[PDB]
Image (spheres, coloured by chain):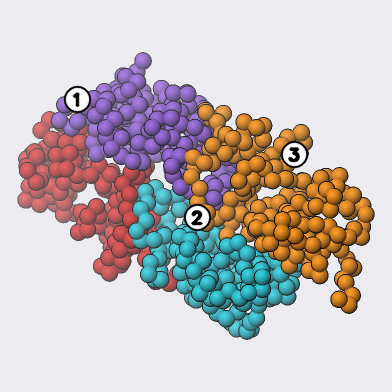
Chain colours: A cyan, B purple, C orange, D red
Amino acid sequence: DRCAPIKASGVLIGDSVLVTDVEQARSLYSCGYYGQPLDVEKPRGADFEGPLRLSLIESLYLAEKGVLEVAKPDGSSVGVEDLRTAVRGNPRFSMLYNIYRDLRERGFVVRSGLKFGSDFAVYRLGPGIDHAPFIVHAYSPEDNIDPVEIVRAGRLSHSVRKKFVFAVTRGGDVSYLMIDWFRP
Amino acid sequence: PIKASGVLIGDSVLVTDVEQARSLYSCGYYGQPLDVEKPRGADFEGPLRLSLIESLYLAEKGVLEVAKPDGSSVGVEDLRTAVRGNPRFSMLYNIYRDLRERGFVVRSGLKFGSDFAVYRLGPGIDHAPFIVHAYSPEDNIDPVEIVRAGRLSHSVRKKFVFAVTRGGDVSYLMIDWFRP
Amino acid sequence: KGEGEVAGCKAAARLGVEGVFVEECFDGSYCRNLERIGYLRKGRLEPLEAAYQASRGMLCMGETRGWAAAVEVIAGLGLSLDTALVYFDLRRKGRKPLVGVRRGTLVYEHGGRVYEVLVLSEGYPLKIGSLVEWSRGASMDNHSPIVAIVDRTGLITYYEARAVRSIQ
Amino acid sequence: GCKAAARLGVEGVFVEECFDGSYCRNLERIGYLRKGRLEPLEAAYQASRGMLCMGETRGWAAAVEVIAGLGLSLDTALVYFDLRRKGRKPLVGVRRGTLVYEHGGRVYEVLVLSEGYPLKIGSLVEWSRGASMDNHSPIVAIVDRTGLITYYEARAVRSIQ
């Protein structure tokens, strides 16, 4: 689909970016489900007051796509590349980021997986709308894991949908392992 | 005062006498039958499979006599080396030990997406274990991992346990969901 | 200037080098309140309480209102965005927290119990050990060990974390 | 009462006596027993089932001898059994740790992993691509430290689907 153009300013404070103008706030939430409102957990679509918090990796993405202008509290501008620094300076964020970019670039709506015990929760249409067919955990292909962890996954995915994905990333490339229970 | 003999194969010890297999599972719920996943208490034929960690504790306690495929005797320290020789099993063993000693029956936590399932009477009786994830106090974690845990214990009982251990001493972190 | 904007605020405050200072009280009961619970003592407001009352729109910081004012105190005084959030949440719930004596902790009393909350933020790993000595720590002072995790998006979860020698 | 007896070579099992002619005939049929030679993993399976004897050693005592004798992996063997019980007919595949079997006219590649033996995630992805590039449906089999076996299909893809 084709939402609109944009469009939105925020302050960089801590590792996150706040968006305090209410219309921008609802704007972004309604136009791609970006950010998270600081007065409501699970909003009725986009009736909330905000501010809308954006995760640093959300931030860099929106900045990149010329949608978000980030400023520091003193008013001074924060570059795309300033953001690319701050994200590349946090191993978790760093691994996260290329998977987000890829997933958003594939047209999915990407949200925090926290409530399903994983890194990303991934929707076709969006939260409250569809259901999130996919649960993602992020990994460098150099990460070690005990095989039981694979099961733990099939656990996590037990109650929502026995199907979770491993999203592996290096050198800005990404490949995903579909894993679903199976009967020989 | 049960006594059983097992063969160390791979990283486990198989108990092949039917009466001994049934014996351990009945007197302390050790081991896992290979012919029954969830054995109703005890019609099952075995062989009983024992974990390496189980093999150590019992050899230590004097209940199991372990041997290699060729019949030659594997001593307590042989097991203790192999156990110490394996990183995941060396951290588990300490906690295993501490919990068995305190009188808990300690089963695998697999079906609960963790390290241990911990029973006060036994599986199929107690009806309600503890869920334990094992950590060395030098292990780094992301604070979300504390949430993924509270999520894992959302179905069972939203009270799980970080068990921290180094060089043989163990403490426990009781986590459980809280409303300010 | 021309016309100060005092409509809607229940008080107005300036940001000094170290601290928020209340200069005008427009609702007396409001200030009197902020003195009975100890946040405001002789105009001096406690930085988090000051960021908070901003974010309700009840405290102006000059011509700056609401969250733009919250961000002002917050950045200005060198606070932590997550701590402030867990604070707000806690203020909103009916608690009156103060800064605990340990790094990253908030302390608050309720129902005859004192509660010590450690604020942690996705992306900022910590040793399990530390989590244990802190909880220990906490328990020794007669606080109930609380952990508040704010995920990368701003969501907050609360968990009691009790250290023990043997499960029970 | 064994339907057959066999003895341990240096790299193989070899059936020495067929007490029940029909039992061996059947084994040749499905292609595990050939010219005296019984495939190690099937050989162990029959022993477990009490069908095969090793000299005068019977059952899982019999099997323990084969596995350890031919240096098989306990976990692979348990998996092999499990798949046999379920009524499949696998055979030791190419890649390390893998058994291969067909069913529904499909070819399934099973990779046997064990609690306590970490693998890098890249590896798993790789193996997974390898399986697809052989028209093998990639099946991972996990055996926790106690003997519980779990199966999953593990498919690598460039875009979620």
Q: Quadrant of the C terminus of chain C?
A: top right
Q: Amino acid at mark 3?
A: Glu
Residue at (47, 23) in percent of width and height: B103
Depicted B33 relative to depicted A80: above or below: above
Callout 1 amino acid: Ser
> Which mark identifies residue A157?
2
Say which of marks 3 and 1 sits in front: 3
Q: Which type of secondary structure does the marked residue at label 1 adopt?
A: loop
Picture coordinates of residue D77 (x, y %)?
25, 45
Query: Numbered disc 3: what chain?
Result: C
Do discs 2 and 3 share a chain?
A: no
Looking at the image, is A31 positioned above or below residue B157?
Answer: below
What kind of element bears circle 2?
Answer: loop
Type of amino acid at the residue the image marks with label 2: Ser
Chain holding disc 1: B
- In the structure shown, which secondary structural element does the residue marked by tag 3 occupy? strand
Q: Quadrant of the N terminus of chain C?
A: bottom right
* Residue D49 visible to the viewer: no
Please state the horizontal and vertical placement of residue B130, each as a whole percent of the image: 52, 35
Q: Give the x, y percent position of residue B88.
A: 36, 41
**Which of A108 and D104 lies nearest the eye of the viewer?**
A108
Residue A54 in sight from this viewpoint: yes
Residue A2, quarter of the rendered image: bottom right
Whether residue B12 is situated above or below residue B73 in the rendered picture: below
Q: Are marks 3 and 1 in contact (CB under 8 Å)?
A: no
The dot on residue B73 is 1
Residue C167 located left or right of residue A175: right
Q: Nearer the viewer, residue A73 or B131?
A: A73
In the image, which is nearer the foreground, mark 2 or mark 1? 1
Q: Is residue C134 left or right of residue A180?
A: right
Q: Residues within 10 Å of mark 1 (few under 14, many from 20)?
A: some
- List the residue tagged with mark 3: C109
